[PDB]
Amino acid sequence: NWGYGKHNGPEHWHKDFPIAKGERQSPVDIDTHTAKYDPSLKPLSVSYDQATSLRILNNGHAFNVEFDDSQDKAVLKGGPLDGTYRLIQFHFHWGSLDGQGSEHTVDKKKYAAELHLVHWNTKYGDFGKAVQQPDGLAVLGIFLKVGSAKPGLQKVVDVLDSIKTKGKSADFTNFDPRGLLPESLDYWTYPGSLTTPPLLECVTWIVLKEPISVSSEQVLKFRKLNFNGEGEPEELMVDNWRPAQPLKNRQIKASFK
Ligand SMILES: [Co+2]
Image (cartoon, rainbow, N blue to C red; front, side):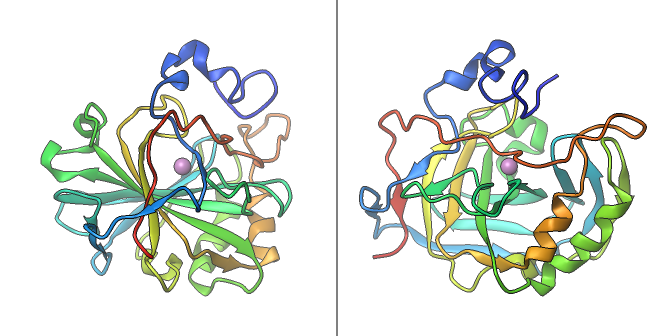
């Protein structure tokens, strides 16, 4: 029964999910002066040319754009990753105001939103088995700032009025996630967790340094979604971000000098 409010939000999750106070929780603050360039990282490879989306779903916490991951398509590899990870879905975390919304922070700076592209390690056969493994997942995180519109986001924006409330879904085919990526693949990486219950400690995080810009009108449409179900009192879907968690002696590596 978890959420982001006063009585069910991040400060309460540890009761049902004690891993919330674990040794490799996410998100974290990225202290850019403490992160070390790692010259042994091979280039990151994001290969989304054959990505095939299926549906978009309001799950009562965010919206998920889901992909058909039944074939070797939409693959993340290289960088800190061993082997190949396959895209399963993406979603966002965002604020009630432009000054907050991201989960990761950069020298304490909060962005207006954060995009998470979730991939599972193909050595484990599927997502469900992957989330039983310490290297089961790789999440590519991308910061959003408010400025110029992101043309590739508009198809997502325009479908949201059909999934206003918890439990609504719409078919959502032929969406190209390449249109959501910034120019540079410079990144920070560290071992962490899912940022929503069950907070599983399976994730190699790859957080891009370059944000994308989205327009005020685009993020305003995110903020018109509802946490509640149809026919329930309206609670706007805003501030669905978990705050930074203790680093606990992990090291953040930078892909760039
Ligand atoms: Co997320």
